Amino acid sequence: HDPLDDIQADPWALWLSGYRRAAVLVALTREADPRVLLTVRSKGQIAFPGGSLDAGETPTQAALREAQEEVALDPAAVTLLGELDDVFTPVGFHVTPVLGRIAPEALDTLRVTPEVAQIITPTLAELRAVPLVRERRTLPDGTEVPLYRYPWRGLDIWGMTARVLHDLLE
Image (cartoon, rainbow, N blue to C red):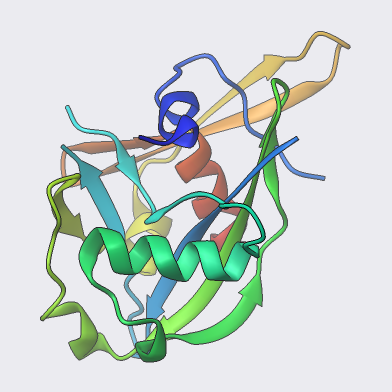
């Protein structure tokens, strides 16, 4: 059990960018029409493979470890491309989106562990074409903040995940 999973399911926790640390792996396939590896947690919580860093662990190590423990993605099958800006929520959670590239075929033999119900791979083009939901909420200090939702194939990608997805698409 991970605290990141609790906070991620909180409909009201706001996420933005620009003390508890975590990381998510954002794997993109090496192809003309790039897909992104996402999971549906055992409506299920849609999220990137990931979780809190253990003691002495870096964001990258956590991201790679989580993707391997969750869907059996071999770290060596991932080319690290750097990370997007950290996304965070007021309470005290910082998430580092660790970017990586995999061969499209790598997706075929992944295996879901009990924590994950299924593996979904939206194409970046599809996420871009979907009727994005753009809302806004105000933080305690008066700071406005955008909130996104990506309606894909009947599933609702919201919260921290949609926030990273949006930074990624930009």
